[PDB]
Amino acid sequence: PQPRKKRPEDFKFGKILGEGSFSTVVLARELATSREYAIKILEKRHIIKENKVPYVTRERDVMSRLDHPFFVKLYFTFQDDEKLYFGLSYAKNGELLKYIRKIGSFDETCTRFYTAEIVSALEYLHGKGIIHRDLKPENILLNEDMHIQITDFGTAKVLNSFVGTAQYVSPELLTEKSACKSSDLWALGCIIYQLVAGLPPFRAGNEYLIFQKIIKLEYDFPEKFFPKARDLVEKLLVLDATKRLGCEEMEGYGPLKAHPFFESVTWENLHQQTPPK
Ligand SMILES: NCCCn1cc(C2=C(c3c[nH]c4ccccc34)C(=O)NC2=O)c2ccccc21
């Protein structure tokens, strides 16, 4: 058995957290328990009209398979005649992009801690044969205890039809049109650069100009960029996808976690550690 299927009437919906093209995330409090959930609401007619059923289905199926603290949890689903509802963890401290903008460049201790949690999360995800394909600060949420919770899985791939946010797109996605774990590792390199520098590495006036810089590996490190972090970024932002730290061709997550930038990191229990304030 499982809990009774929930329904709209079981909740007091509150504010809209955000709105997308095919869905809206609304904060809702379950009446019988007082628990707060971030409920993603999708209109069936619109999903069907735009051929998004594979994506919506993928979002639900991938999230159902995840069971790790660094990922948003899918607690339940239900639907009425017009909409689909996905009950998700409500990450109280919002997204990492907000935090980066709020504080600007992170010092080395904060960069290390959050980079380690993302690496640890990717190790888990890739270990299950799942690629995110749209990893960016906006999709990395912060829970009440300031640990990360990664979300946005509709565009994930379970091991060449989707391309994520321009600034985090890998060269292989612009040249060969194919999805690999290497693309998430490239995104990781961009994110580490962004935490240290305050902005992503490839920036320009429009998407075409950004893609142009990406394929030519046209970016540079600002002064004072932590040396070990720069070395790590240089080993992730590599045009040849098979040579990025973390790839099976480079012998996996072991060598990545062993990079000097992570020397003081205890990988086994990051989630029990107190995030640096
Ligand atoms: N602008 C946030 C975009 C990322 N995002 C946040 C969320 C989530 C949350 C949100 C938390 N704050 C938000 C602001 C805008 C939109 C969504 C949220 C949340 O608490 N839990 C989530 O999974 C989300 C869910 C599915 C797909 C993308 C999502």
Image (cartoon, rainbow, N blue to C red):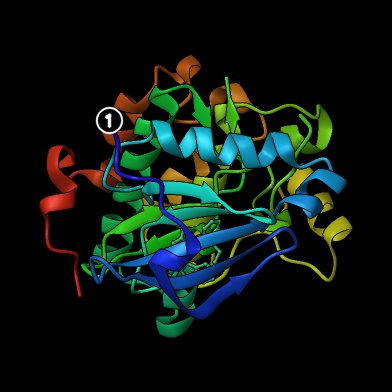
Q: Position of residue 30 (x, y in %)?
A: 33, 67
The N terminus sits in image quarter: top left
Picture quadrant where residue 158 is located: top right
What's the amino acid at mark 1?
Pro
Identified at 25% across, 72% down, the residue is: 34
Q: Is residue 139 above or below residue 169?
A: below
The C terminus sits in image quarter: bottom left
Visible residue check, residue 196: no
Query: Circle 1 is placed at which residue position?
Result: 1
Nearer the observer, 50 or 213: 50
Q: Position of residue 129 (x, y in %)?
A: 48, 22
Q: Residues within 10 Å of mark 1 (few under 14, many from 20)?
A: few
Identified at 34% across, 45% down, the residue is: 4
Element under disc 1: loop
Identified at 46% across, 57% down, the residue is: 7
Nearer the observer, 28 or 61: 28
Nearer the observer, 40 or 122: 40
In screen coordinates, is 128 left or right of 181? left
